[PDB]
Image 1: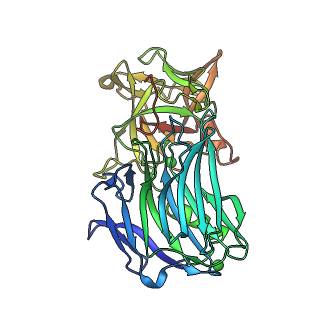
Image 2 (image 1 turned 60 degrees about the vertical axis):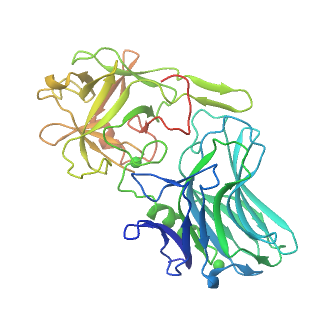
Image 3 (image 1 turned 30 degrees about the vertical axis):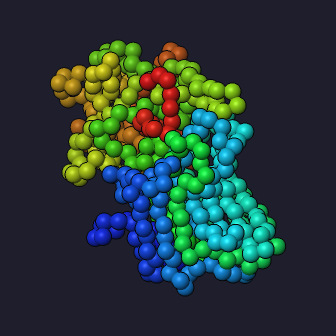
Length: 421
Ligand SMILES: [Cl-]
Ligand SMILES: [Cl-]
């Protein structure tokens, strides 16, 4: 759909990235490309000569035009910058004889930038920029998967959409003929920092200007909404430790008062800060008590957490794992949660239904499969204790805001460095 003229997608039969658009453009993958073992569409391009992908376009879809509209879309994940770049570097190039289109990255004045450049055969350039600050407590963008869509209307504007939403437009109507290349080079080109890399997936080209609705539907269809995601946007997994971010108070972190059914877990603050003047100023994410999601009812062989999976939650306390559990017979709607010894869980409630996209992800069950409530928090004499509460289940269908039950799961990731765990 959408006049797609290139659709880079992993194919099991040939066991490689191929063009699935129907035009059979050849995809040459360098030896220095790395792939995710969990999602084989995710590819990592590092700052090495062999870490490159080259597309040899079907000769009928090469762009050589003054008036034809075209669009591109892709997902990208860019590590946090710890050093000034001021050093714009290419990542996706379709240029010949100084004409064509190009995606480049830069980091300047605490802003990470994604730059779209068009250049016509008279040498006239137009650029459109998406940028985001590194001076921010918790970013929607730093080191997290971003869905990018760039549309080009030769009569008027080039537009950048980010996660399905128009965020910038620049006039391109004065550009003349644009004669782009026979091939597309995916490769960090001109980057002076040897540690830089990117992750990318699902690169597409379209020979029209996509509209708002097509882009939102593209964002949704490529989102894999049946699979829960961690904070970085990767697949949520079993047997993987996660730090917990509560979106209703993000400046707090999780702690355990004591283990055992008489103890409780609670949110304390403030979150720390990781700071270097004129480079970054962020809240620390690798803090507090870790959760590990454990398989219960799911029979899938793989370690991917899916919508409506029934799981156990283990809690890590001084390098030892306990079970998140509660006695559903305690008084009140709010059931205070405990970290109990795994052999001693007995008949305490412990089964959690995981829910993908609000963002309330954990619905605790009793052993009749009845809802005890989403896991959130509640104030008990100025202590914000962790609770399962059916108040959430009655409420999150009424409004569309953040609730105390809205969480993100944060694993340690190479693209986000901190001193303390
Ligand atoms: Cl169009
Ligand atoms: Cl999710």
